[PDB]
Length: 113
Image (cartoon, rainbow, N blue to C red; front, side, top):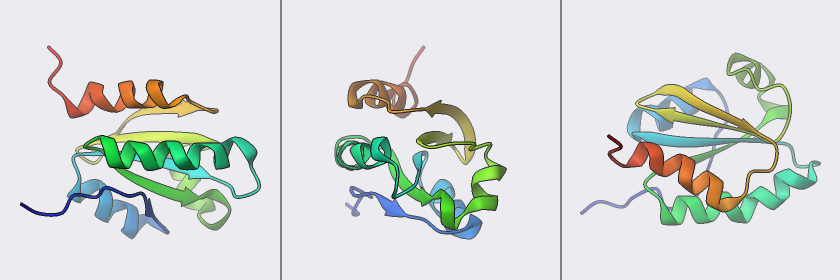
C-alpha cells in the first residue's frame, strides 16, 4: 500500500501539528528542549515508537513553539501528549520508559473492550 510515517516528524507551529493529528489517527507529540538531558534520551525511544507502532510521532521544540506548548498545557520538559482522532487524550511528563510509552500508544492503536 502507501508509506506509513515510520520516522519522527519535526513539527513547528499549530498548522503543522494539525496536519499530523488530522492525517494520523494516533499521534505521540514529544515536547522537548535540546538542552534537556532526559529529552535527548527520549530521542531513540520515540524513533523506535514511530518505527514499531501505528502512532505518528511529532517532535516539538518548546523554545521555538512557546504558545503552541502553552496551548496544550505543556509546562516543562519532557512532556508527551497523545492525540486520538485529533483530540488530546493523554499527557505524560518526565522520562517515560519505552515499554510504558508503547503500552500507552497501543491502548489507542488497538481495540480495547
